[PDB]
Amino acid sequence: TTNTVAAYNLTWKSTNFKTILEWEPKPVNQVYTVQISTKSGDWKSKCFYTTDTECDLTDEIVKDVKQTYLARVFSYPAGNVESTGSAGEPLYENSPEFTPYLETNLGQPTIQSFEQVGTKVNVTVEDERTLVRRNNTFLSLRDVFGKDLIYTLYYWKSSSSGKKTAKTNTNEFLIDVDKGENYCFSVQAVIPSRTVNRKSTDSPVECMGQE
Amino acid sequence: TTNTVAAYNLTWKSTNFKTILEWEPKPVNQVYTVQISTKSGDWKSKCFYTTDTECDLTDEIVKDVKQTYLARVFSYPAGNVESTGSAGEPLYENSPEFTPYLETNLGQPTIQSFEQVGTKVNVTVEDERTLVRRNNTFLSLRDVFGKDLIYTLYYWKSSSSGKKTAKTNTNEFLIDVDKGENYCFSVQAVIPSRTVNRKSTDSPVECMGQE
Image 1: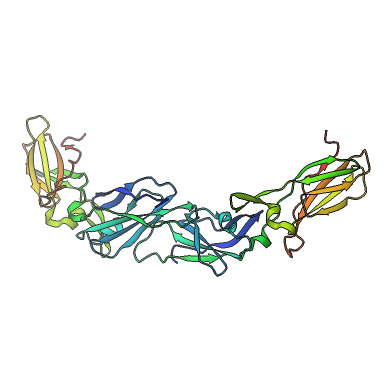
Image 2 (image 1 turned 120 degrees about the vertical axis):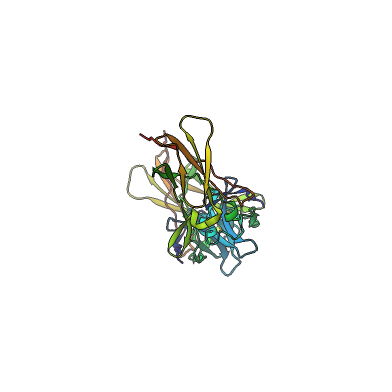
């Protein structure tokens, strides 16, 4: 219209289900209103008449991480408008589709602790808490993906050659080490069943004699 | 509703037809939208989703200074709203009625010039330009009120006693002075036919030997 431009570059920013919709451009005499819906669903307004160029949609997508979502950003004129005729009203742009389950990014994992139990070392990776709520509790990464989530351990002797690997479908690894040694490990989460965004980044590395 | 309060103290600020609607309160997670209509007329939006606590309605009231106007201030939720249920929407408050012709304030007048033409002095008051538009020109105060506007001259000898008066229905006075003297004048506009807001404030005073 004569006082409004449609938003563009509607991109979804989601890591561990924390979901923000980002768009352009920084407004001038214009405010936005962001709406969300499951594909083919009712539309619901979340961020109202704001000058912000992003909207946190976590509270809604978390209602059912399996649903496919669609967002709509409206452009509204702001301030003392020309009057004369009448401000045209409601230009909006639809976001790309978002299936949180299949698309949220797996954040970088953290090794919680390792301990030597004989010739065996037990590596526990931290269970990350999410905002997915069920009953009166927040689900963890593991609680949400269940058997779909897998961890990979990379460990190598502080000295050399290659890194050996191990995988687990729980939050812990139990491995055989060359006794009385210094080993370093790092872990990476993976969702094998995904065609895209399958892996996370490696956790920082931890070593045996951390002193 | 659960996130919005209705505006209050809707007061009209108008001097020489420059008309601003002022209201309370300073918003928090809320924006306003101001609409105007002739009493019983169609509503038109002027200031959109703003955080401002005032709206300049001059461009509209000036369309017909004789009409009676009414303004409506809506309250709209702003920002990332609770979601959960649904933001209630549209609480609004109507302004008192405003008839510009009968109500705008007469601004302080300015004596443009005085000159001695014999035993006569001619005092000219400045014709104030307004935003009232007609064809391709801006009307002056005089052009709008015509015969309803009147000026009063107050003049007194620089020495003493009382101030004498004179009235005119044009922009100038022609008075008889005690020759070779020092006189001071001040002018005040008046619209006698008004029951309220009849007069303006006195213009600054000007004197004969301004040197």
